[PDB]
Amino acid sequence: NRETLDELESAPQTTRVRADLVAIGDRLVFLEALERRIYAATNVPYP
Amino acid sequence: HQPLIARDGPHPVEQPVHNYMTKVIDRRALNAAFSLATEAIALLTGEAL
């Protein structure tokens, strides 16, 4: 038929966060280098 | 104090660590002089005016 019956959410919490934004052409992508953030002293190699 | 990250499956399990090292102070003394000549003494302290 025509289904289109995927439900929407409840407009969740929108916080401000220092992340890193660039734009490549039409698309707008993060940049993430996760060494000093999540892997600093953890002694597990970067994947 | 260090964090850790949970490893999934066939690895040893990472438990936390705390590292303590004390450091000992270096000591050092700086020397510097300034002289004063003999005829200059008797003028400033008096009893040669």
Image: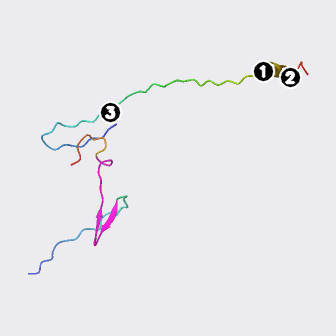
Q: Quadrant of residue B22?
A: top left
Residue at figure coordinates x 11%, y 81% from the top left: A2
Closer-to-camera residue (B17/B31): B31
> Disc number at residue B43?
2
Q: Badge 1, how many Cα within 10 Å: few under 14, some, many 20+?
A: few
In the picture as drawn, the residue positioned furthest to the bottom comes out as A1
* Residue A38 image offset from top left, x and y in percent: 29, 48
> Disc number at residue A8?
none
- Residue A31 on the magenta segment: yes
Identify the secondary structure beneath mark 2.
Answer: helix
Residue type of the residue flagged with mark 2: Leu
> Disc number at residue B18?
3
Q: Chain of mark 1?
A: B
Q: Are marks 1 and 2 in contact (CB under 8 Å)?
A: no
Q: Quadrant of residue B14?
A: top left
Q: Is residue B20 left or right of residue B27?
A: left
Point out the image quarter for the N terminus of chain B: top left
Disc with the residue nearer the chain's start (2 vs 3):
3
Nearer mark to the viewer, of 2 and 3: 2
Nearer mark to the viewer, of 1 and 2: 1
In the rendered image, which residue does mark 1 sit on? B37
Residue type of the residue flagged with mark 1: Ala
Look at the image and give the residue range highlighted in magenta: A20-38
Residue at figure coordinates x 23%, y 44% from the top left: A45
Q: Chain of mark 2?
A: B
